[PDB]
Image (cartoon, coloured by chain):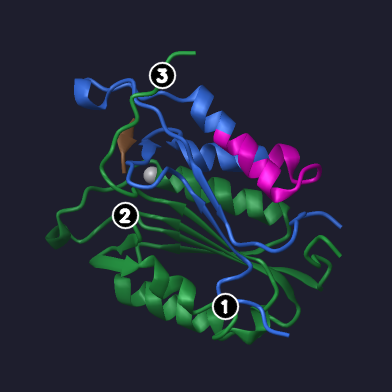
Amino acid sequence: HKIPVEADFLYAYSTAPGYYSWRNSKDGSWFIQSLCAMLKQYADKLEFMHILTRVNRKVATEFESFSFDATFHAKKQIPCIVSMLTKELYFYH
Amino acid sequence: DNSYKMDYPEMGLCIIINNKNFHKSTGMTSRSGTDVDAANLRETFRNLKYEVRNKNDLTREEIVELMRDVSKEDHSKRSSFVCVLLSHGEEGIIFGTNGPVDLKKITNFFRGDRCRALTGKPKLFIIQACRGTELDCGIET
Amino acid sequence: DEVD
Ligand SMILES: [Cl-]
């Protein structure tokens, strides 16, 4: 009869709660780079959560910061999928 | 009936808010490389058949008005809604060019309550922004 | 690389 007012929202965060998020001044942010690449490759193949999981893996494995400042050097990032969705989401058909 | 109905006449809006330059009074740095993101997202969501609208350097007042206006459009023929936020942030907060906006304030405009045309339709918020000041040192495999 |  009713659904929750918070249902059917998805928050695709670039980073985990409490953490900095990394941006590259030449290539763009790690998260958006990876999100667009995975949408490009898989939007006609995978459900959105599985696309976003490939994004998590890409950001987690293929990026590490390089900084002249030791405090910010060699750091890592994991994005954070927050799903209140009630159904699978496919971009095709 | 396990998947969202995505065969309405339109996939829906993709609103991209690209905040690169902030008012000097805020003391916030420019976000070099965010234009690369904004263009990448525009092309990506174009290929998914979203009606993309790119907005640049919006104040906190403009962000809220934009979200309010967009939530009041006719979404009856739209399958979904996407909003991409590219800015400085902290936990629960994204920054307009002159000050912060609570993420809850933005998303509440689209609650199944306040935007009936999107009830039961997926509302996707993609957020490139800090959520705090912690650094992840990683671990070897 | 920059935090942001
Ligand atoms: Cl840029």
Provide the secondary structure element on which disc 1 rests. loop
The residue that label 2 is drawn on is B89
Q: Are discs 2 and 3 both within one chain? A: yes
- Chain identifier, brown in the render: C
- Chain identifier, green in the render: B
* Label 1 packing within 10 angstroms: few (<14), some (14-19), many (20+): some
Provide the secondary structure element on which disc 3 rests. loop
Counting every numbered tag in the picture gives 3
Q: Is residue A70 left or right of residue B113?
A: left
Q: Residue at x 33, y 61 (%)?
A: B93
The residue that label 1 is drawn on is A5
Instruction: Tell me where the magenta segment starts and ends, as one range.
Output: A40-56
Q: Residue at x 75, y 56 (%)?
A: A88
* Closest to the observer, B69 or B106: B106
Q: Distance of mark 2 from mark 3, alpha carbons?
A: 26 Å
In the rendered structure, which disc, 2 or 3, sits on the residue that comes first in sequence?
2
**What number is the disc on residue B39?**
none
Picture coordinates of residue A59, whole percent (x, y): 51, 32
**Residue B123 occupies which quadrant of the picture?**
bottom right
Which chain is home to disc 1? A
Circle 1: residue type: Val
Which chain is home to disc 2? B
Picture coordinates of residue B73, whole percent (x, y): 60, 84
* Label 2 packing within 10 angstroms: few (<14), some (14-19), many (20+): many
Circle 3: residue type: Ile
- Chain identifier, blue in the render: A
Q: Quadrant of ligand 1?
A: top left
The residue that label 3 is drawn on is B139
A46 part of magenta stretch: yes
* Label 3 packing within 10 angstroms: few (<14), some (14-19), many (20+): few
Picture coordinates of residue A73, whole percent (x, y): 28, 22
Circle 2: residue type: Gly
